[PDB]
Length: 18
Image (cartoon, rainbow, N blue to C red; front, side, top):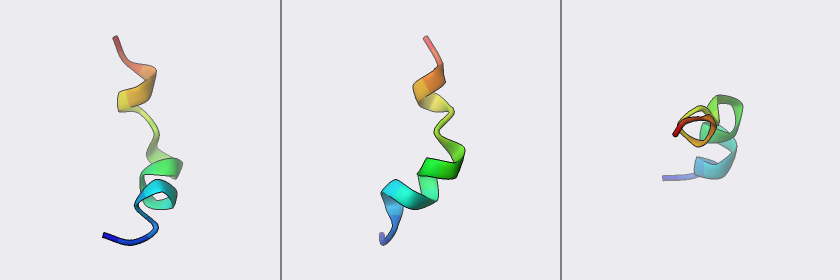
């Protein structure tokens, strides 16, 4: 995909998990 890092950026949630 494109802007994947940007697309998921706005989301960046799974990263705030653990």
